[PDB]
Image 1: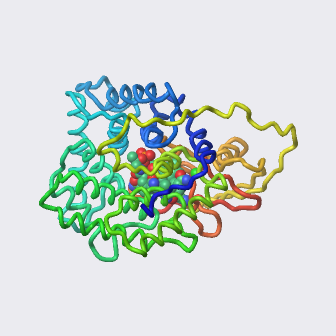
Image 2 (image 1 turned 90 degrees about the vertical axis):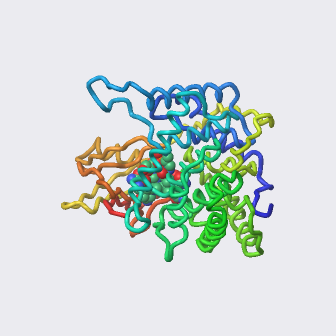
Image 3 (image 1 turned 120 degrees about the vertical axis):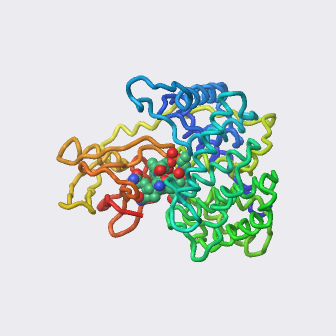
Length: 414
Ligand code: B12
Ligand SMILES: [Cl-]
């Protein structure tokens, strides 16, 4: 397929996999990541005996956290439960090991996911006013995860996603847009291939064409679909063909070229990003989880085991931190070694000054939730920008500021 990546340098692929490798040893509840496991299984690489151990740890964690103790011992909280979107990714990890969800525990998890989607459908409502409590991204992911296990949702559930894709100047905010379209597209694709909602067949077919149209519309002059980090998900979808056009073929050539050029510059550091990219580089997508091949050999991944000693005096950078959207504005000047993350900078400011911040765990790493005591509310988030007004494309743990940058933390409501 013209949208498939064929010409990748194997040593670049190995380098990407090597970044995932140490995560295979990070087995705590808040570090376990079903997306990383899926990513490796659909790649051309393997982390040996570490993989099965990782999946056993996922099985233990998700099952014990999400299932039972009915009369919960004086708390109603303490454990750090995975979310329902995270449960969907867990269902994808099972498929990646060529398993179907089964037994009583399995049926219980399936019910919890179906209930999540039903609660989301009702939050949307009558089709008009109402957003999901989470996102259309997670809604799409839930449908897809049930679908690859051959579990059906009601026509009305699929209907809310179809409507969201269909109706006018579209619902989707710019940040989520390409990624959500790609994930919606993959759900539709699974539903079409599996014939789970036959009464919606034609509507699903048309929505698939519409998703492709919107993704192409979002191609940047560089050739990314949306941005570099949404390009792997979009290519996961577009490799699934359907409607081959010359416009699509041309778009895909530009996108693969842009993605390849970006890989030459160590662009992908975030494990979750790598996990979405590795399948594309092996001509696979989440839709392949309908009938996975666990018999196909993968190349063994070994660590670097070297680590570069300069024995030097490092270059320093001067950065200005700024906080806006709260009543008294805050600014902080720090000088740090070149290569320090924004997270390091925030920790430095908290240590050597009156800055304070809090994060919560996510599959993408530390998510910024509070700044100077102000926790982000219900439909609010702490947006991270390079001044002026340019939202960053990496989170706090991965963004490495350059000399003389002013970074802004802005409480916004989207
Ligand atoms: C929906 C979404 C959001 C929502 C999430 C809130 C909501 N109502 O759900 C909002 C709008 C708040 C958001 C914010 C941001 N996002 Co966002 N987001 C997504 C999206 C579309 C889906 C995430 C999801 O639900 N995944 C599934 C569930 C099961 O996973 P999860 O880990 O449990 O989900 C949580 C995290 O993803 C977290 N989150 C969302 N975005 C980001 C980004 C980072 C870096 C981290 C650590 C966490 C995080 O919110 C989710 C819980 O609500 C992804 C797309 C993708 N390809 O993954 C982008 C994506 C993860 N976001 C991205 C970015 C860059 C950001 C921001 C840094 C943008 C900015 N400059 O402020 C901020 C985060 C800043 C912060 N406060 O730490 C990038 C990350 C790229 C990279 N190199 O890692 C992605 C890949 C999109 C893209 N193509 O650029 N995001
Ligand atoms: Cl990254």
